[PDB]
Image (spheres, coloured by chain):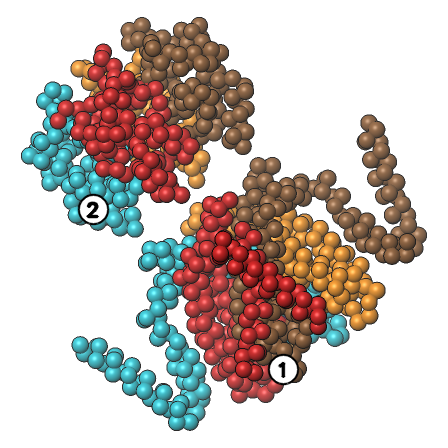
Chain colours: A orange, B brown, C cyan, D red
């Protein structure tokens, strides 16, 4: 099948004419558009342009549509070329995406009034329950700032996306606490003056020993509780120092991408 | 020796004909297979394909079999080319790999019964010992989840592989604790009200000061115990913050590779 | 428009003559300067030089001035080429930048005297206020070392530049402490022996639980205070372990760039 | 000056003959050695070899000796080429490097005897001083293992090399402790029940608050001591989390390079 020669600043490219006919609207696929760059003396089309980029521009046609930016070609440059060669806004975006008492009442009432008002205006434009209700509505209040603080949105999108990541930290943390709250429970017990009788309390210690917080409300006195204490102080920093790189790589990405 | 010219979208490659005969089954090595792409006018074989990839495709023959994917060529693309040129499933994989009271009894009995049953069904398809036995079988129980929790397998494979890494953390931790539990022992002693008489107890402090847990069950009161305490708080975070990058790079790899 | 051919060690480049006339002072743009490298037999200018670099050297003219160093070309090499081709000191720098009781009184008086003297010599060359004044002038004294200690300058430039980064850590820390000092306040209260009555004190705990310092002056005794305590020990290490990579990447850069 | 053409698997290179004469012993510089690869029909030397590598092989001569391995060319491959082209062992290495009661007495005496014996055999093949002598010889004893433990050597070489790095951590730690042990000293004092009278003791707290160890032997009770306590818990983790990446990058390098 009749072949074409494209010269990009001395670098010669060759393809069949049907390969370019696969995208009739692009500059190279449109006879009338590329006609301006034909050299009758050499029988080739010449372009005084960026050499590194054309590799992909041609592969686009041969691949049926794949438009990847060569790793060694800047983003601003390669974008200009896609524009010049007239690849089309569709493929253009596809590339883009593939590439990237009273005072308390007054304050409480004023907010409920403003919030509801603003909410409605924008939208339109028993004894035991009282204990659980105050901890809910009053505690999650801070979440309102997320609507005016860019940072929170980033923190949220990262959590929603890296949920599987966090799920491991907690999971691994469990197996850890369970294994340590048990290994010390068997060596800490059967000894007087030891504040490690039950297991439920051994859970707190472990959670306080793995995160390295160490309040001092519970500490091993026996030899068997210290051996598992050292392994715990280590296993903790080891287990915790895992999902971090992931969440950070996600946050830093969501942060840099949003900004 | 008679040479051949291969034109890949304008980029010309040249090699001897025996070099290609070294792999008679591949497309380029098989006369009958490459015959379809010969251009009589130019005396060369033409391929309307990916330019960046062919560099390696040719080196494969010249190297006697080495099939490396150019750093600047996507994985999905280069794979297609290996397929087209018909390099062979062997070399193909080789590339792949080179590239990547009653309730307690009931619960206890039910499990032992189910586990043993499931185990057998799947397979077929004195006073001091009682103290060490309860800490063993009962503590390692959690390890059963590893068979239904992907995460654990990753954590295990990383440990089994980065064993030499962890061995250092503990090793370095030793030398550290030994050096600190001794430097403070000589400056903390010979002083009343000091809870640092013996060395074995100095070990606990050091292990609790390097991991930065600091329960508060032991703290320097002398000037010589604080100087070594500062160096300890530092040396600890320095020694611990070493094998981490390795274990993480292993975990993150085993995690991303498994997923 | 009359075209030119430039041969760089066998690699042929082609451009129009006006493209090179866009920078009349450079070697390639100056007829008298490039005349020395013209080959009459082939009708092309030949240069026995670095191939990888010329890609950019030519793009410079086609782009109207863009001078980027190819990712695969060393800095010392590409710099030499820019010099040879005589691109010009301007574009040269632009590239550079786009690329990178008595003793107390005596001591106090002597300093004030020396400092003021040195300052002037270099420049030319009520009861409640006394409490706030001593904490100010006397505390910020150390900042004087910054003028003789390179390290501080780096620490400062990184802070001044990554201010938005730090602003998040503190911000996120707030929302965290507010949410935790409240979630535990509702579960820690309504229970005797609990040292978590007020909220202002719950703030201290949270700040001491998220940074993982854990002095032991405050710890959850209830079940509801421990559940939020575990989430706090985690959320803390998660929130803190975020701006770090940024500040470090800034510090390490400012450090390596300054040195 | 008479020019030469080198064809590397279809990729044509051109240089002057003197450029190659600059290294008379290499294959390309030796008439008798390159004669075997000359093609009389095309007037060029042909090599059925790796294309990516030759770029550097030629630059070596043009540069007067610079032998850099292209970023996109494997180490094992490029090495083979340097060998084939016969560049010379010198340049070869240069490239390599540019590229990479009684029991106590018995035990004490036996060691002193063995050590001194082994030392000599290998080499040949008052009251206050007693307090400082026991802390020295007895404490640094562990350092003997470094001769049989690879890990320590790595830890040492990294310290000796990244000394300037560590010097900052300690330095920055100083300025920090000095600024915090002073900011809290002015707000913690003038208040009863406060364990922060003197400054020397404020130093311990700061060092225990920045490393996040928090023994609990000292904690702010005033409002002014807590505000500076939060800034301290942060500034600490910020200052410490700086030299880490450096020491790690050095250790990981010294570790991977040694192994
Ligand atoms: K800690
Ligand atoms: K701690
Ligand atoms: K603590
Ligand atoms: K504590
Ligand atoms: K305590
Ligand atoms: K940490």
Q: Can you give x and y, in whole percent of width and height, for residue A243 in the image?
A: 58, 49
* Closer-to-camera residue (B7/D222): B7
Within 10 Å of disc 2 (Cα), the crowding (few <14, some 14-19, many 20+) is some
Which is more toward the observer, D234 or A125? D234
CA distance separating discs 2 and 1: 69 Å
Q: Label 1 CB, ligand 5: below 8 Å?
A: no
Residue that numbered label 2 is attached to:
C92
Residue C54 occupies quadrant = top left
- Look at the numbered disc 2 and give the secondary structure of its residue: helix
The residue lying at 8 percent from left, 31 percent from top is C35
Residue D124 percent across, percent down from the top left: 49, 56
Q: Residue at x 66, y 82 (%)?
A: B193
> Could you say whether the residue bearing mark 1 is in a helix, strand or loop?
loop
* D80 w.r.t. B210: above or below: above
Q: Residue at x 31, y 37 (%)?
A: D91
The reply, left or right, for residue D150 in relation to residue C257 is right
Query: Is B257 above or below relative to D214?
Result: above
- A212 and A47: which one is in front? A212
Q: Give the percent coordinates (x, y) of residue A136.
A: 66, 61
Left or right relative to A99: residue D126 = right
* Residue under the image location 51 percent in, 63 percent down: D237
Q: Judge left or right: residue A79 versus residue D221.
A: left
As drawn, C1 above or below B84: below
Q: Is residue A179 visible?
A: yes
Q: Which mark is residue B191?
A: 1
């Amino acid at each position: 099948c009749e072949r074409v020669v494209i010269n990009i600043s001395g670098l010669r490219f060759e393809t069949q004419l049907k390969t370019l006919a696969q995208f009739p609207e692009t500059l190279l696929g449109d006879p009338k558009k590329r006609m301006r760059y034909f050299d009758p003396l050499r029988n080739e089309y010449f372009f005084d342009r960026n050499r590194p980029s054309f590799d992909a521009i041609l592969y686009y046609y041969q691949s049926g549509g794949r438009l990847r930016r060569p790793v060694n070609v800047p983003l601003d440059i390669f974008s200009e070329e896609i524009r010049f060669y007239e690849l089309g806004e569709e493929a253009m975006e596809m590339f883009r995406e593939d590439e990237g008492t009273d005072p308390f009442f007054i304050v409480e009432t004023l907010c409920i009034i403003w919030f509801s008002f603003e909410f409605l205006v924008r939208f339109f434009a028993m004894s035991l329950a009282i204990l659980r209700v105050i901890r809910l509505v009053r505690v999650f209040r801070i979440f309102k700032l997320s609507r005016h603080s860019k940072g929170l949105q980033i923190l949220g999108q990262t959590l929603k996306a890296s949920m599987r990541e966090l799920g491991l930290l907690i999971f691994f943390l469990f197996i850890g606490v369970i294994l340590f709250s048990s290994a010390v429970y068997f060596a800490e017990a059967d000894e007087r003056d030891s504040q490690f009788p039950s297991i439920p309390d051994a859970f707190w210690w472990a959670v306080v020993s793995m995160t390295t917080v160490g309040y001092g409300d519970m500490v091993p006195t026996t030899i068997g509780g210290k051996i598992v204490g050292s392994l715990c102080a280590i296993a903790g920093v080891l287990t915790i120092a895992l999902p971090v790189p992931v969440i950070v790589s996600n946050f830093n990405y969501f942060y840099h991408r949003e900004t």
